[PDB]
Image 1 (cartoon, rainbow, N blue to C red):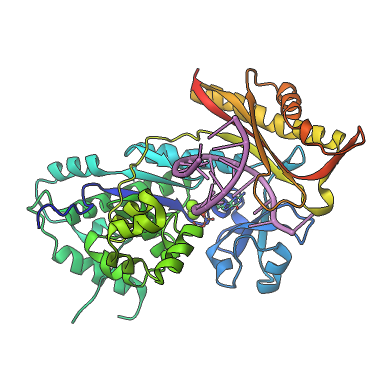
Image 2: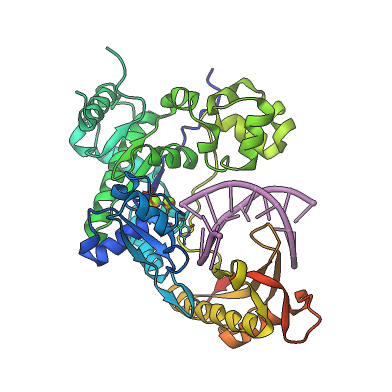
Amino acid sequence: GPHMATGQDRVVALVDMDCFFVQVEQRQNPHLRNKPCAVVQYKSWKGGGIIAVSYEARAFGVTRSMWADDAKKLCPDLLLAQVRESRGKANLTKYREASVEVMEIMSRFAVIERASIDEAYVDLTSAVQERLQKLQGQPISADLLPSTYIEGLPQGPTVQKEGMRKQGLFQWLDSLQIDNLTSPDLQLTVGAVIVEEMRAAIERETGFQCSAGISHNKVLAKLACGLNKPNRQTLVSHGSVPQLFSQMPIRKIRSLGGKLGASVIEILGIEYMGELTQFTESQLQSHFGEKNGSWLYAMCRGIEHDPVKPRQLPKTIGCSKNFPGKTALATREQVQWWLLQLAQELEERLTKDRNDNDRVATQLVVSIRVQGDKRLSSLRRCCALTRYDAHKMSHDAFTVIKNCNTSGIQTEWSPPLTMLFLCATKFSAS
DNA sequence: ATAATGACGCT
DNA sequence: AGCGTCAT
Ligand SMILES: Nc1nc2c(ncn2[C@H]2C[C@H](O)[C@@H](COP(=O)(O)NP(=O)(O)OP(=O)(O)O)O2)c(=O)[nH]1
Ligand SMILES: [Mg+2]
Ligand SMILES: [Mg+2]
């Protein structure tokens, strides 16, 4: 009864920018606003690979990782902006700084955890408490939740989206128990109000629009965020879960999108998140290991404990480049040359990092791919990073991989390299 | 010829 | 330490 722990202890939100790279490009170039458009890296191979798509472009079937030439076939009026190129490669600096604008704004409200270049989680538990004290005990008005959806409402005894949304919101507020300061749903509601505010501020001060999820944990906040994108936020209450999970494919839950999620489907013979409830913890631990079992057992009940880590800053800093097919690096002059290109970008990102964030990386990781290998990395090797010098860093990276050169000739490089990757890690205060 | 990255688990 | 998985 009262000792069944229910995962309602926290209030956690996930804010993710809408078609981010696109909005960055549209803020810069007014011509691209409210039009089908996409952002590509490179231009020579089939017009370039798409990495971001406005919603007007999505409505014609344009997706991430489509070639730009194929995309034009679906959507001939498609507008494109391409990623800056420096030192012979894609440079993402404009989106990193645009990201920092967003993160700095979110930081104002609460401690965030940077989960990607375009999203952060927030623990709103404390701020909800505060706002709750300050609102005395007066009703919460719909005018404070102008973009909020209540997952699973309306239900019970208009045909347009705004109509439906409001009915849902009304039902929820009409049944909200305001006098009870310890009510989880009331807390979510208040969290949701703050998130409206946070989103108003982001758009006011950056001109960028975003979606958000408000729930009791990260997994649910993330899932909820996706439900009503673009430019809308979504409250997933603890009670909405059984219905939500009842037809939620397992693959849609964070960290279940790959192999583990496949074996869950496969071993258990299920499709949806909620069918997990029929398994005892021990059983799921038997199949999926002890951590996964535990995590799965609670997750399918909407309970998840991972905390919102106070980390606004990346722990690693990295430059990488693929050299597909024919362009696979095949001489020792080439490998050196790109090591230097990568090294030089890395150097300028680190000097900026050290000035901005009062810290130095202490270690360099070197990673490569050989032709005829299947995985992201063929090989990783660490060395010291003692100076922010592109020559030393490039020289040293070379040093630690030269032995991988299987070639008999002096100058040649075999097998040819299909990837080079440098990553600075192990940071210490500066 | 998706491509550039970032986080984290396992051993 | 170096590899594997999952994500955006
Ligand atoms: N370079 C590179 N960037 C990528 C890749 N995948 C995503 N991004 C970049 C480009 C993305 O703009 C940014 C954030 O990605 P999301 O939030 O996953 N999708 P978005 O915000 O575009 O649209 P929405 O969220 O509304 O559906 O990360 C990639 O494979 N490579
Ligand atoms: Mg996004
Ligand atoms: Mg995202």
